[PDB]
Length: 108
Image (cartoon, rainbow, N blue to C red; front, side):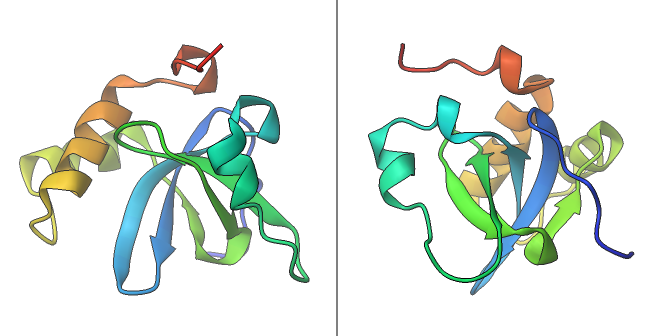
């Protein structure tokens, strides 16, 4: 499970404090409006800006809490989501339909 190389448009899972791995894809500040750009962390370590599902959000997490999220894993969750969070389930449901970053909708 060594570090993984995440590319822009790749669907990955980002775990947060008190938050189960969330379906988020690695994006770039180019697709992050001012809301996602304002949360850009300036601490040591390169952080990956990802889009969180659903509602296409934006989070800056390091590759450490980032894991590769395959479509199969996403669908498996749809069959059984855990924990039971309406937002996460909508995350996998909307992220499962979103193939890559070029498919997401940007406020442009």
